[PDB]
Figure 1 (cartoon, rainbow, N blue to C red):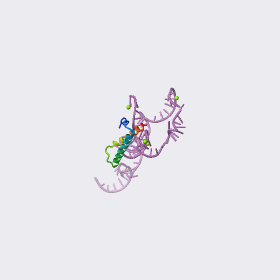
Figure 2 (spheres, rainbow, N blue to C red):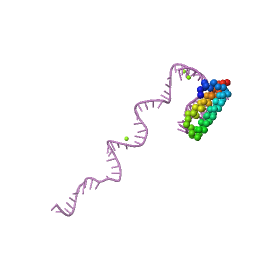
Figure 3 (cartoon, rainbow, N blue to C red):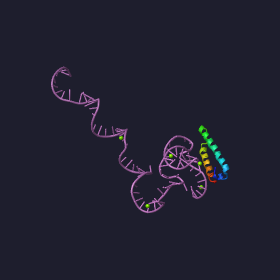
Figure 4 (cartoon, rainbow, N blue to C red):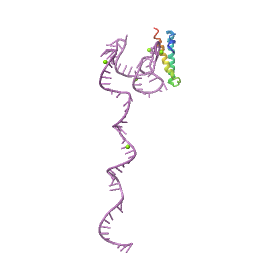
Length: 61
RNA sequence: GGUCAAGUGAAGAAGCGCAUACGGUGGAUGCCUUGGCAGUCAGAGGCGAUGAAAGACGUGGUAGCCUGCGAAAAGCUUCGG
Ligand SMILES: [Mg+2]
Ligand SMILES: [Mg+2]
Ligand SMILES: [Mg+2]
Ligand SMILES: [Mg+2]
Ligand SMILES: [Mg+2]
């Protein structure tokens, strides 16, 4: 999720973008706990998405 | 071919010694180096309340330790190769 596409939004709909990833990061950890996870790379990929949204969310001022 | 007497006296090693040939233990010697020591020529001579030097705990798809990072956590954004 490139930061270039992230600057096209506003703080109002970037904050829901961050909430959407927290669902996704949570759901992936519930699958990992039960052992029924097949897309293992998605754990480290979702972590990077939240960090990038929080990066752009700090630049608006 | 006998009987007797006198004399003489090889081998026979429980274990051991020396020599030699093969092993075992052990780690020397030789050769080697990703580690040190001592100079010369430069650098820049401080870091810290914008939180230092030194750490604890966490951070990975899976157990530990080291090396990096800090709930944005072996990384996030922009430039340049
Ligand atoms: Mg020998
Ligand atoms: Mg000098
Ligand atoms: Mg460590
Ligand atoms: Mg934060
Ligand atoms: Mg580039």
